[PDB]
Image 1: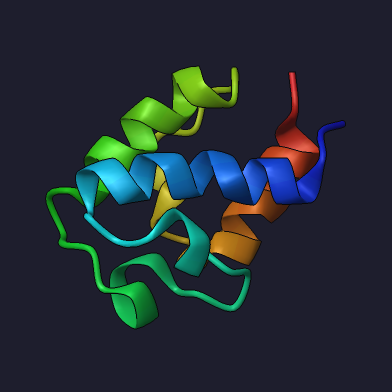
Image 2: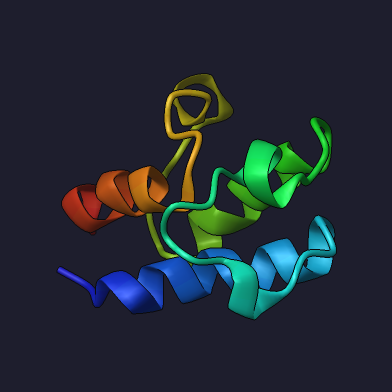
Length: 81
């Protein structure tokens, strides 16, 4: 497995770049394209990058069900390669 906070931080580092939202405000209650407020199209870049960032394969198809940083982590934490 990986460290949940490291997972969230992995999300954060991409979000800070692509979305333009603080690495640090990438908490765990934070819904990416909602509370943080990314963008719809920039969202898919986070996803695509996450695949390499976390070393996993998270398709945009299912990623739409993650909705938060915490639930993104849930996928990654469980789907760890």
